[PDB]
Image 1 (cartoon, chains in turn purple, green, blue, yellow):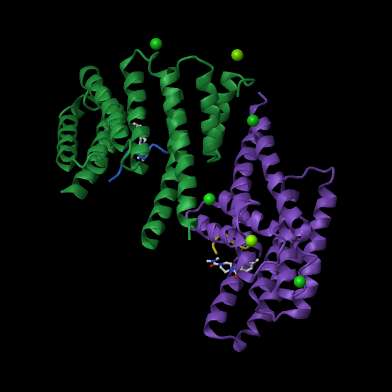
Image 2 (image 1 turned 30 degrees about the horizontal axis):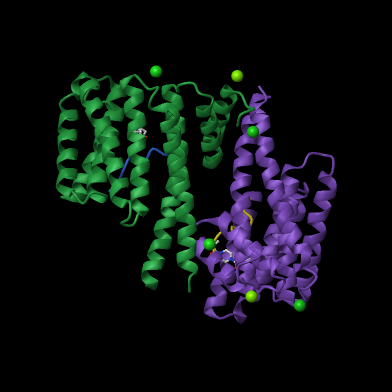
Amino acid sequence: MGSMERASLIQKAKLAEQAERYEDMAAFMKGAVEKGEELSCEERNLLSVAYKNVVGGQRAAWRVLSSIEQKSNGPEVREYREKVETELQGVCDTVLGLLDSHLIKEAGDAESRVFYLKMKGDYYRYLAEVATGDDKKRIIDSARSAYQEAMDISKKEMPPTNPIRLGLALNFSVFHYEIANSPEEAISLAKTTFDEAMADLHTLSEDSYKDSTLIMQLLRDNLTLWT
Amino acid sequence: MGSMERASLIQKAKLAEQAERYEDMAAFMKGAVEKGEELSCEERNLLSVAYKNVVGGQRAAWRVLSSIEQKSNGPEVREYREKVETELQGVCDTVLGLLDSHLIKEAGDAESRVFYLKMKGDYYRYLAEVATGDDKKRIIDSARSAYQEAMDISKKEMPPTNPIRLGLALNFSVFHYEIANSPEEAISLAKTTFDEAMADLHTLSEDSYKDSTLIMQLLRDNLTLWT
Amino acid sequence: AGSIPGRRS
Amino acid sequence: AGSIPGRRS
Ligand SMILES: *Cc1ccc(C(=O)N2CCN(C(=O)N(C)C)CC2)cc1
Ligand SMILES: *Cc1ccc(C(=O)N2CCN(C(=O)N(C)C)CC2)cc1
Ligand SMILES: [Cl-]
Ligand SMILES: [Cl-]
Ligand SMILES: [Cl-]
Ligand SMILES: [Cl-]
Ligand SMILES: [Mg+2]
Ligand SMILES: [Mg+2]
């Protein structure tokens, strides 16, 4: 996207979101990142929404095919699951490459740095979902390490009701439950996150209260499923 | 897809449908067609479902962007609508190329020939939806001519309740209403199609009755919207 | 106006 | 288990 203006790439990313053209959206935001400037709060959201939708469709397809493959256990189901899996890993590697070159190293504010490290944890988590044994462990630790650094910063620098802090804790708890085989850690983190946000709600405006309580309900939904 | 077996392409098209990976599905069915053998009834359905989903997403995105462009009347909205529009026209041209090389000329049975000519009408209709003036008229006549030959065959060779005959009439009526500015022709065709199917339902098994009455309800829905 | 949905088969 | 839906913004 080297010949397109940064502002035009951002404008077209917003258009693609409205048209539910998420592959286009991700390509526009990739081009915007590669212009080399830091991203605004809104721009970080556009980057995240685009790739979350792209990889979300790939993950859903991978699970359908993996289930068919398991039930069957010719080469076609395995071959096609491998194709989808390779395309998913390519998208994850692309996002991780953007974070590493050079979004994270240039992110100095708590809001931007925690946001990018949460992303890094998420896309290693998606790699971990399809990994089998070999570097499954190293991928899992890469996800853990990214989430952990984001957690440490968010606890130092953000209020307990901050939506990025809350969503980070939500996803790290899903990591514990689904990836790390640590359901007790998952439940403990979700509970402590919810209770500390509850106690800080009195400080919020009506609009911030709605933002925070929305994500708190997601934590509650998981606790209800897990206990 | 030249190095993959025909049967493997068909198997993977079915897998892609289950995974809602319709771009993959269309590419697998394109490869199957290009093996050069005629398509079975089920295989024709797979071809049609795949490309209908692909172009359906493109049409939905084009309408979103065209509406934004109209409300605005920089270059970005027009440029991106033009991009989507070009990608849509490419998919339509691909399907039309498959029909012309060489599905239609080798289709001798009424069921296969009407099916392919209905497809040819549909994808010229999709081209007509985005065409502006220049060859809009020639594209419209190409759609009309394909639908008309399919209609002539279906009336001679198929019972009035045949689902392909019914769906052809439904889409040709949509052509009349939406493309050809002939709402009275659209209403007349839908009415006559519905009434002649109603009178032939007594001949059908319970399963065929469900197939036919489903499409008859679609004709009724349009008549309700149009009158 | 609805054409054949034809998105499932 | 639901992660952040994060599909809309
Ligand atoms: C990582 C991350 C944390 C928080 C948020 C966020 O503010 N929202 C995501 C969810 N959401 C929503 O409207 N529903 C689930 C209905 C918007 C608020 C994003 C990303
Ligand atoms: C061109 C064409 C005509 C008829 C058919 C057909 O048999 N069906 C399409 C619609 N359908 C359905 O289940 N719903 C609308 C719920 C399946 C039957 C296909 C294509
Ligand atoms: Cl494959
Ligand atoms: Cl900085
Ligand atoms: Cl563009
Ligand atoms: Cl033949
Ligand atoms: Mg510039
Ligand atoms: Mg062979």
